[PDB]
Image (tube, coloured by chain):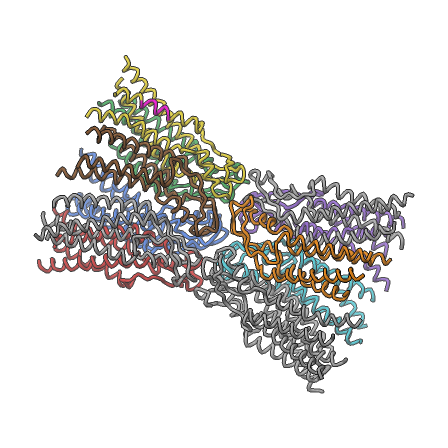
Chain colours: A blue, B red, C green, E yellow, F brown, G cyan, I purple, L orange
Amino acid sequence: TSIGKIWLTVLFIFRIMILVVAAKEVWGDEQADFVCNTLQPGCKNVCYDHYFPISHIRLWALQLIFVSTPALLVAMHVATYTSSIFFRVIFEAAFMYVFYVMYDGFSMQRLVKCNAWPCPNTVDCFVSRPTEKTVFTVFMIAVSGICILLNVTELSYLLI
Amino acid sequence: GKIWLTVLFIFRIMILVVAAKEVWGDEQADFVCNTLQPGCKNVCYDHYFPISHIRLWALQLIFVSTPALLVAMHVATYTSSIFFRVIFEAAFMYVFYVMYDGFSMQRLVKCNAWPCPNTVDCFVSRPTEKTVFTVFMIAVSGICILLNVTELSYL
Amino acid sequence: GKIWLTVLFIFRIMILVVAAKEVWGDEQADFVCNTLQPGCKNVCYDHYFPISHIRLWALQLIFVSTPALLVAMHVATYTSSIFFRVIFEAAFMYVFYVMYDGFSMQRLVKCNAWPCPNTVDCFVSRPTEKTVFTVFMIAVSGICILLNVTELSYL
Amino acid sequence: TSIGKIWLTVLFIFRIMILVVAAKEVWGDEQADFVCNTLQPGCKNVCYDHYFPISHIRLWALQLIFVSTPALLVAMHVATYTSSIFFRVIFEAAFMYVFYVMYDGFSMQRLVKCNAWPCPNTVDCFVSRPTEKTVFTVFMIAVSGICILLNVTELSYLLI
Amino acid sequence: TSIGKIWLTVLFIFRIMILVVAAKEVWGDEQADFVCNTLQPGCKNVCYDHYFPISHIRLWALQLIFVSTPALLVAMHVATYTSSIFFRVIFEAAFMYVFYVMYDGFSMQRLVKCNAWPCPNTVDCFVSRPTEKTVFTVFMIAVSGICILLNVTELSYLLI
Amino acid sequence: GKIWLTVLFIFRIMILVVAAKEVWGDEQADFVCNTLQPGCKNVCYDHYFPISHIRLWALQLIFVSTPALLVAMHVATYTSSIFFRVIFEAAFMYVFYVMYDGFSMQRLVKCNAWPCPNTVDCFVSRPTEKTVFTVFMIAVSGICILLNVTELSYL
Amino acid sequence: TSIGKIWLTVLFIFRIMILVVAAKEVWGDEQADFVCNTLQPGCKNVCYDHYFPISHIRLWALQLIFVSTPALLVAMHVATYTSSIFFRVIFEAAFMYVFYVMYDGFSMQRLVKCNAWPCPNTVDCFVSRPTEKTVFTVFMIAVSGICILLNVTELSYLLI
Amino acid sequence: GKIWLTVLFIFRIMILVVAAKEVWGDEQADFVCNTLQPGCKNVCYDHYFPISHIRLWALQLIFVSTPALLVAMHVATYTSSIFFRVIFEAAFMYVFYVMYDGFSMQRLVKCNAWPCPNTVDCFVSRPTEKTVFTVFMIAVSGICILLNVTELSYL
Amino acid sequence: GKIWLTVLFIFRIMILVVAAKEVWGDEQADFVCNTLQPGCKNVCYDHYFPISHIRLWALQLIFVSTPALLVAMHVATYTSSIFFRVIFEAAFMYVFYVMYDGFSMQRLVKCNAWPCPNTVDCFVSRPTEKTVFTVFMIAVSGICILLNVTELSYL
Amino acid sequence: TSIGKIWLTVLFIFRIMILVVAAKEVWGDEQADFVCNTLQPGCKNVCYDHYFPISHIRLWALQLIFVSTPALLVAMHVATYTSSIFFRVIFEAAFMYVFYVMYDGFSMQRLVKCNAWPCPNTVDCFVSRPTEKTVFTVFMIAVSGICILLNVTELSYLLI
Amino acid sequence: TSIGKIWLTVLFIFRIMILVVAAKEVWGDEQADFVCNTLQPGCKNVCYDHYFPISHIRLWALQLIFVSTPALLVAMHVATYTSSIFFRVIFEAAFMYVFYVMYDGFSMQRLVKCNAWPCPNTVDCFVSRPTEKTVFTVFMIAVSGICILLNVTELSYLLI
Amino acid sequence: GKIWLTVLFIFRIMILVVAAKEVWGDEQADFVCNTLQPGCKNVCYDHYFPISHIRLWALQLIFVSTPALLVAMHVATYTSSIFFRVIFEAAFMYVFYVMYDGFSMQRLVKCNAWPCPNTVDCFVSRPTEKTVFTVFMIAVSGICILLNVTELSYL
């Protein structure tokens, strides 16, 4: 109802700044910060790929990428608007579906045990600092849920 | 009033920058756990430093720069935006004092986390600075509260 | 038509940035050769990763942003600039598929290079992502081809 | 006498650029460049905190921060001027007092011997490259002394 | 013939972007990525200085530096033009002469054997990733050859 | 005259940038002292490299870009600003030649500092480049002197 | 039948010399020669104690000790003879019972996987050279079986 | 009686030899203290293993083979030599049980000695054997006591 | 005949002693497997050196000094003791040649055992000697066979 | 009084066996078992030479050597007897004097702090297992004191 | 001339004791004491086998072995004498021939440079303490030369 | 006279045994060269310790127990055997003093051998003892000379 387009940009910018702080001074290169109790070359890297196929940061990076493309299409069409919202919804929903099916959040595995091939046996791989992630997520998740609801609202109003 | 808020805002930003980049840095790497047991250190971190000071304060400025944007958007709630700007800035203090029990920085913590074979001496690096920079980043918050309380109450 | 080209162009740029900076990174350092023989790893790199994906795609965008500049210069050849913009973007795909035999990222390669005393297990790091980001950076190319084929043929 | 406000900005910018070169390609992360002849976890970090409580760079960072706040207050008052100078003096004096009482400059301890608790005994901790600091300081000190005198001058003239 | 001044700037920008990607995500700090089969302090550094006196990146950096100075002189003379080209040619030719006499390209030694003084004997020093250099070069060379020919062309036309 | 000064000024800036960032770098870390005695290397640095070339030249450009700012300030002394601009640029040469005894870069120095148990071989890294870049950064200074001498004398 | 007392001493001496070669130039300090794929202090020692409570060598040492005591008692009684045999049998039988119930021979675990407390997880501990043990055993076992049968024979004859 | 004493004497000697040479060995080296603090291990030894079992038993056989030599010397006190031979052999048991609190061998001890930064896990090696060999070397002592008590009392 | 048997017997003993103590030694420790994978080396031992030469020959002299003791016992079968003394000494040769495929000592073996990540170069130490000492310890056996064949056949 | 010559040989043999067990399975190569909290080549060796100039074992070795020479002289004179005792006393007294002035026993420094030249500073050197030495000593000392008194007794009786 | 059989046994025993001291407290396990400036598994072992095929100690061990067999044969023949000398000569001559052709003595390579296959290149392998070998040899050589001459003398006298 | 020779002979033997086995030991391993250059230490040994004291004295007793055997052989030259027994025992002193410049043991030597990059501090271990044991093993020699001089001269 016209207020929506405000809170969308507010939460958009907010989620962006959070995504920056996350990627920069938290996640970080996590891996390196991924301590595998072992001595078997590739055990750590493979356990990481196994339990962190697509890191949270780059999922969210892609989330904002794809879910800022239709809103850019409209800007070109001017100088389909409802369609760009529909997209802006299902994408932001998709990146959430893949998230929950992958990491089974919102928690953040404190400790993982990997039995990958290089690894001689089941070894204790430690995640690094994961309260300060389980969280950021939360925010990056909640913000997405709201950003859904507002877009669904506008979409529904425009079908009236 | 409105002047000193923006002054201390920019001031706290600059302080926060210097803190994050030079003082704190990647505190972890700069964290020395007397042991040899993979993950004792990292866990003893997430225990004694769940959310680092820098990433609390980043969030502080974020959430406490959000209401001030809503007013600039309505101009195609001000008093409400202040109310928010207060309770957030208060909350980010509450979580701070309940968590770290400041304003002092623990020079040394002893961790008996599960990975750790036993109680081990984990050293923090450069706690004196870190304290100073909290002291500033806290005092500034207290003041920013007060000025918003007088502005809000006056109106 | 012209719109979706620029959209997917900027899109592929952003994808390429995230890839180069966060995903790939300095892949090498993040490359773990089960051995202890100086240069076994590096050689086994230049064998199985002659030109990294990032520095192919950097060149892709370069060469496939060159014809589009000639037209802006003539304005003190357009159809020819498209023709180029196609065959380059096709070439950078040909070299890709002939080289790495994608679209999948080899999880593990076994190198018997000269420095290596024998066949040794060299592990690649994080191939799943890397695959995903290729899949996007390839699909985008296929589309960018098609749209230029319809635009070129139409004219 | 109107020439003062020029040389203030000149020396201000000069000290800034010097502060950059200092922090970036000299001091650096000093610590790391702080070689403690030992093998006792935390001996180096504690000796460092003991003998470098607030590093020179961040003292000076704070110096320019606080001593560019009143000069910003006036810019807001326009769109008290003498008061902003008084502040601009006593602060720049304060950051000098704390400096001399802390590091007893202008020299720069080439070598320090630390008997902190973690350290088993008195150990030789080495500072890293300290001619190329003892100096920069000098400059960052002298510039401050001048920047005092010019502000005291203006302040005194304005009391006439 | 007026088209020249276009393709010069095109190839100039192109070579620049290539020089960036080269220096940043390829060459890199090569050295570090220079594996000397040894254990003798300074053997690697000296073999490097011996076989890579002036790295390719900084040769090319200097190439663009010197070969963008006359074209800047003219911009000052306006607010000698043929002379600035003559320079722009012989310099770009010089940086090629030094290149071929130094590295005997366009190839890129995959492996070098160094018998420098620190080194106890002839040791196998490995260059790091050199298909992905032998190349970039190629480009940075070919572009230079073309950028010569176009400038020689303009120069010759202006002598008519 | 005034033209070639600014040309060579910007030129020397670019040279200085490349030197500081790529050639010199953190020279220290790139400094290999044949020993095992904590602080032998660092001291042998501050002995044979008191003020690195990069941080002399940074200061050179600073002090020799200061007088040229005073004139832009007076415009709400020019000849005096030149005189300064000469004697500084001369001084930064004097300290250079008296200190390092250039223009050559010492390939290898032998340090018998106190931490060092004895005379030890400390290797410098990549002295040939470093020499070249001094040669340019020195020649440029000599020229910048001459042009200011002719401009100053002419007036 | 009088020939027995010969072959007893023959096989006794034979088993002794074999026990020497075993303990000296085979078993050895086995442990040290017990490679636990790990890095967790005490994992190897505990896995060893778990899977080699009483090493083979010292079982056999004790075997010959106890099973040369009655045959010494008789030598004192002279300067009960059947009783000393009965003992000499049941002991040599006992040291075999404990052997088979402990190591489930005659094989010799080439590789053992230990999940002891110090060990972070199930880790691959390697036994060292175990064809050249599985064997010696065999001999030290077979010899015992024969040394039983001969003593049982004499014992039975003397009950007639 | 006199027979079984010499039998069990020679027996306990052989047992003691095997213990000292193969089982115990240089126990220390075979002692694994979860730490990295020079002397934590050694001190935690002298605390939990003041006098090793082998060097108690060596002394046991020494002192309990001394009276039996005096009688062979008088023959150029026998009952007195037995009395001694009893009280010594009893004493070497008393010190054993009061010290180690056997007959079991402590599989694992946790030491908080001064050198140690904290309580650390020190592992003993091969305690099961060591127990067995004590069990024999103790039982033998108990018997050697009894037989001397019956011989002494009988007389 | 009987003389030269005892001569060559004592001779082969001395040779065997020097071999076991100085030449072979603890061959293992003196065994250098180009790898870093716990147990690759040990397994590659038990594969390529199931029963070391020293502990075959120890057994050779044992079993081939057993029949010669039975005759000294019967004297409170001689021809039978020779027959045994032959077939044993023949057997210990058969197992040798079928196992190691001598008389040469493999300078270098390449092991792809399970622990090993791949085929790795395991070096043997000092194979030339070891060969020589086999050559003697084998030739001696061949002769000791022949003399017993002539003595046995003659009778 | 004739009983003396018995208890001398008894205590002589006793002290010998104790000296064996000491040197073999206790002292050992002590050094190696001498843990100097440092990383400075020669600090440990020099601190050892400083605080253990002549190890206890070799003092006692020499003690028995010299104090079994006169008792051997008499055996040659037969195939001066009082003189050989006088020697046998003053020597055994000498080796005790040097002992007490050197190690200030009977205790055994658990921990020593060495500031020798190689050592950068006062460092904590740890002695290895010293209850099980402080002791043996005791015995090797007491036995000497008795062996004195018995020889002094005989000597005095023979002066009557 | 009857004096020969004395000096033979004298020099025999002398050479034996020298051979003991050599093998025990000099040569030693030399290898270990064989420092190859490298880091390439097997380079040291192969260079050793290359330049020390049969170590000096075991050549000499074999020398005394073979050259004490005929002198034992005669002892059996009694309870051919000239033949046993002839052997005793040619053998002791043989072990000298193999020695000089192998090690080209009497010197003792202080330093050897090995280019074996495992070794990446020509590497500096250091022999350990070789004055104190070049020597012992000398003695073990000279003694052999004399022990030849005396046996040749006796042999010649017995051919008269 | 003849008595005290054999006394001091056996005495010097026992001293030599204790020296070789416990004091000196494998001196090398117990030799600490402040460096990291393969073979600097070993060479600096053979320079400052060509023939170790133990292996000089072993030879001393050998050569100075050889003449005393010739006399026992002639008994199926005595004065000549003494003369030899003197000049040898004198020679083994001459080589000692000319070589090591005793009687003191060099606590510390500084080696600039070829392998060594420079002059490096090589520490000797336990020189005080070693001195003492030389002092005895030398004094004994001086006496053994004197007694043979009086015996030889008297005759």
* Placement of L131 over or under C108, stated as above or below: below
The answer to which of G152 and B103 lies nearer the viewer is B103
The answer to which of I106 and L133 lies nearer the viewer is L133
Magenta range is: E87-94
Magenta stretch: includes residue A73: no
Horizontal side, residue G48 vs residue A110: left or right: right
Q: Quadrant of the C terminus of chain A?
A: top left
Magenta stretch: includes residue E93: yes
Residue found at the far top of this picture:
E160
Residue at 34% across, 20% down: E149
Residue found at the far front of this picture:
L154
The answer to which of C33 and F4 lies nearer the viewer is F4
Of helix, strand and loop, which mostly describes the magenta segment?
Answer: helix
User: For residue F23, which quarter of the picture?
Assistant: top left
What percent of the width, then of the height, locates residue E12?
31, 27
Q: Is residue C1 visible?
A: no
Horizontal side, residue A16 vs residue B82: left or right: right
What percent of the width, then of the height, locates residue I122?
60, 45
Q: Is residue I34 visible?
A: yes
* Placement of G58 over or under I3, stated as above or below: below
User: For residue C145, which quarter of the picture?
Assistant: top left
What percent of the width, then of the height, locates residue L103?
62, 58
* Placement of L120 over or under E135, stated as above or below: below
